[PDB]
Image (cartoon, rainbow over all chains, first blue to last red; front, top):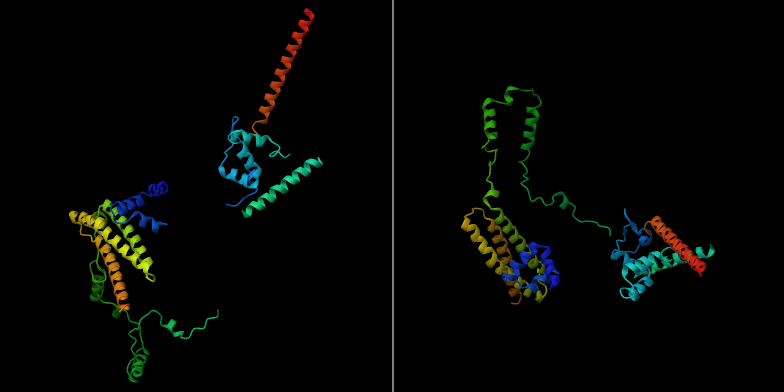
Length: 309
Length: 36
């Protein structure tokens, strides 16, 4: 319970969603939670040093990560901690002793041999703890005419077309540039009218500010409803296609949850719009999606019934 | 591990205090034996 509660607190929207789905008896908490569900470096000793502050401050910063690394590399330190802390000595006293002991301050043949042995032992402990088809298509013409549907490609008449080809060939064989014939005042006025605002070319015009027509609180509620419906429908479609009998029961439960959500949350929200008489059909998209899901489920049920005939 | 100069100063102060205490003790012993 404690683990479950902390998850809701971190995401207030999910907690609000959890309240709207479970407290309102739309879905059970069990079904709600059913769908919801370091290397070791050798620098941990050399880089980690007793930090000296401005005025006699031993800033140990004894993070548990360094302590765990020391325990992994040096089991003797862990044994001493277990056999001394917190009865024989305190943790800080043990750390001070370790700093003051020869174990940390390793710094002449005997001394060199001891240093070499310590380094080899550290390396060995670190190493030990580190483990603990040719394609040949057939019909390439499909790429020549791809997803483009069959167009209106029409072949002309018989040889007479060539004669027409001759006509233009004879028409533009003796050609002279013209200036007045290019444009006329009436044609210019017609073009301006077409290009004038409100004309045929100027399609439509200004629109309405839908942002101010829908209150921001209603917008947030619509967003929350959209998120909830989308998650429920994603869970519904995840089962599809239904290949096992358990998926049938799961989809039936999902449909029941969708109906409960629509009754408990969507309908009072609808009146919330209807009481305000907003002309925006925000609920229309939700209704379309819900009806599409219901029709898909009914069609699949009909297919299942027919397969058993 | 922290301010080695401060630790050395503390050790020197302790040594000076011990030397002064030993000097006082030996002076007292000298006075007592002279009185005896």
